[PDB]
Image (cartoon, rainbow, N blue to C red; front, side, top):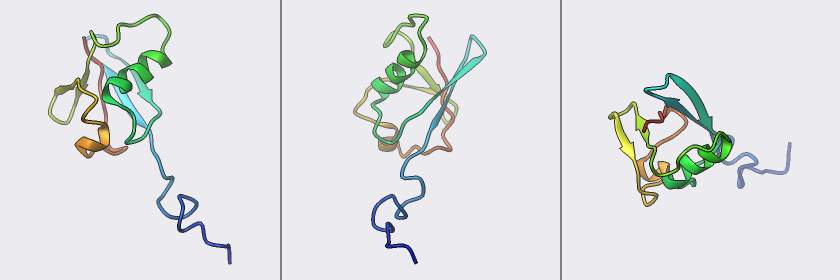
Length: 94
């Protein structure tokens, strides 16, 4: 047996979290975010700009979404808010 855990992410959900992949269009390079349905979109870029270090603009830049080739600006719509999972491939764009 094994206690349970099935109640907490110790067996309840899969890994209890996931990652994200970003793509820099117009530049053709790529970077990925390590986050969950909790990172603010306005945080997805920071969590990303924060990951990098060559001093990249924060809000000025934008993430192009291959799903609808649109852009993610407001944080009010977290990835999860949109219903995004780890099967969501993001992009980066000016």
